[PDB]
Length: 238
Length: 49
Image 1 (cartoon, one colour):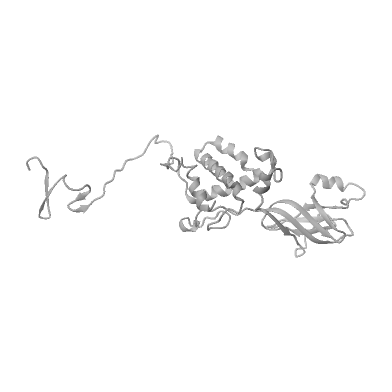
Image 2 (tube, rainbow over the protein chains, first blue to last red; image 1 turned 90 degrees about the vertical axis):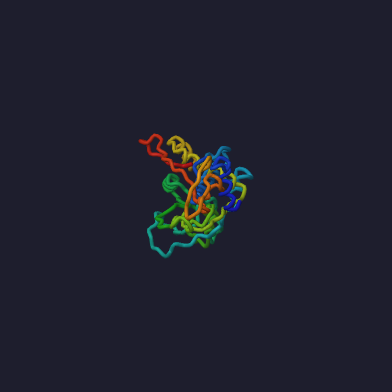
């Protein structure tokens, strides 16, 4: 659905079947609600417990087609420019892509061979560093996040006696805003996420209906003005 | 004059309530109606529709 279809069809649902019976939303407000709705839909359909089916990213064909146009593969760049301090002796700091939303697969190409990266929690790190050897298994590497400035920096703790030659990251790209008009034309300097012009949906058409319905629900709740409605539909913001 | 209402302006006699609607002396004049909307006036309201 083009942006013009998202605006026209919001009023067949929010505005009492385009009857001007409900309050009436500007195009900036519709754009804001659509952007928030798409963020909510992505977050809910990612986590299995966030949706109504109990199914996550790759738990059904529908979920696979939902995130199909967000999945991106990018390389990490060595953060040798800044001589920071790492928590681990053998940690090579790598910076991740800027348009990163959620990581789902990471791999590192060493001289010994490719090794799947395990994002290791702060408890497992303390548990595995209390042992004699203190290295990953032969076919894996660890990863912990470190001091990050306006980006995402990750320490790659690969086994000693090995050098990192590559670092591939497969992640969900940050969705672009949904904007139904040139905001600068009538609204002075309002931006949704830094873009003031018409922005289409960068998602598969399968979830456009989901996003529009969530936007309509959010609009109706924000206008009913009840605290109860706001807190109830705020549950699904995550 | 008899059973009809007349007016005199600019040197001509204009029969009243006989021309086309909203046409006074050959010129179109607008019509409007203003009404204050104060229901539960202590309360602050968002006027919507």
